[PDB]
Amino acid sequence: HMRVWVGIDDTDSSRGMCTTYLAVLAMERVERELGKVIGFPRLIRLNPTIPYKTRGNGAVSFLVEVDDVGELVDVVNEVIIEHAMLDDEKTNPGAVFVDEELAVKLKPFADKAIKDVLQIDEALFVIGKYFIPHLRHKKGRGLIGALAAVGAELEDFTLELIAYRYPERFGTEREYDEESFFDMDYELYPQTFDNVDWCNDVVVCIPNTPCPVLYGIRGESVEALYKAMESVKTEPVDRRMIFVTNHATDMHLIGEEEVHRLENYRSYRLRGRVTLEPYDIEGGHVFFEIDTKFGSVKCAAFEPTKQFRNVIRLLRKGDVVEVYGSMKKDTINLEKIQIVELAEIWVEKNPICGRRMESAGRGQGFRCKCRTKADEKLREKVERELQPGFYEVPPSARRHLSKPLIRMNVEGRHIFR
RNA sequence: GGGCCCGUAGCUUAGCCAGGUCAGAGCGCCCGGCUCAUAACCGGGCGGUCGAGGGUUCGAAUCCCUCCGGGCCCACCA
Ligand SMILES: Nc1ncnc2c1ncn2[C@@H]1O[C@H](COP(=O)(O)OP(=O)(O)OP(=O)(O)O)[C@@H](O)[C@H]1O
Image 1 (cartoon, rainbow, N blue to C red):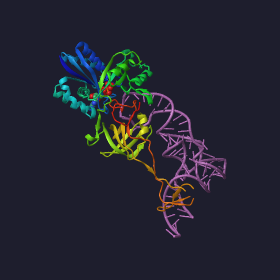
Image 2: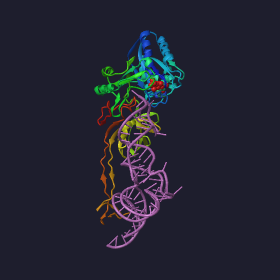
Image 3: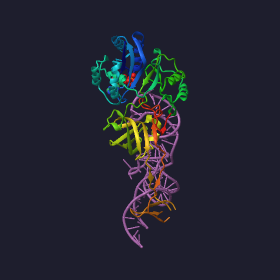
Image 4: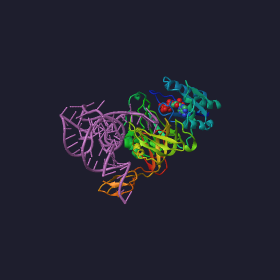
């Protein structure tokens, strides 16, 4: 007997199925034909800016205890040769079978696949250092996510109960009783979180894709996911599995503290002062700029962000903030932001008398219409509405890796349920 | 004492000095849609009679008179 970590990635299709699903099918075969599957499988989300991602850049791995690693590999290669969309060109699968003892040695790699950008060669190099049995299909871009999935270190993590439909019910649209999910959220939240967007009315955990996935509930315990699991009404649940994921951890973010430049296709946490004030563009798309330890940084607050814009617009030149987000097209697409300090803002106004006064020459104060005389203008402090604290985008906007403010222990949280 | 600017839906604005689809548009808002691929025109709807008053004309947001409100400049007196 031996302990081997199986890792899989890039196997789905635009029109195809899910990668967690194929890992479940392989698991079943391992469980009854080769040995046992130890504990909960793992869904490790990686760099959410990769262009190759089919929709979320999620990779899968699971511990196994088989008698002979050779058969194991064949068995898994098979499940791929049958349930993997090898047809598409956006799908280049890869599988890894690393010995448990060796998993740890991959934390640096997985880490680099989550926060930065890697290359197929880099994955093949790791494989080459420990002669890790692997499966490279076509290009094999999957070997990246595969290794990562196994090496990814979870110091923090959330759980996710994923239920799949019956095969015949595929393609067709899912049938379910919405209202049951709110009863569910209204009864288990925060425990189970990011499952519904009230102030935007939506059920996020229920996809609308070709994927076998019926629904997918996130929580902080099996207890919650369990209570939730039965406390909901939907079509009959065929297969179902609970995954340990780095979902809602911010494992992708890079503190400014730890780097010099800021490259595109990466995410960070920065502090800065609004140099240029907020502003829209067709579609409800808000933008602004902050002065940073790097220079002039621009922040995007796209429409899908909803109620977030209602806060961002309130930002004024000179405010101190902390922006969390990924950078693409040289901009930081806000996922959440902290309002550290607010800059007061005054206004110049011409005096009165009867009524208001005008300007009498460049250096000659102001005179009435009311025939009077005054020297200075009416300066006034304009109280703001915006307030310091942490503001995040709404549930329906959340990105898998994005840590919801409900999980963070910081004061000044304005939570959007 | 004189000389200018500017005011079109809640904002920001086309059109205005070539007056005859008297009202276009982006944001907002109301209402939907997409998606648990951070996402640079996703939609529909309501919404202005064009600062106020007045005059010319077959007719003005659109040319003229003046007023309200914003705001500016040059001189003079001292
Ligand atoms: N940091 C990275 N650098 C380079 N390539 C990466 C990186 N992270 C992931 N990849 C590659 O991006 C591709 C993602 O494809 P994949 O099909 O896994 O998307 P998915 O969104 O995970 O699919 P699904 O969510 O439907 O199961 C894989 O080849 C993965 O190896």
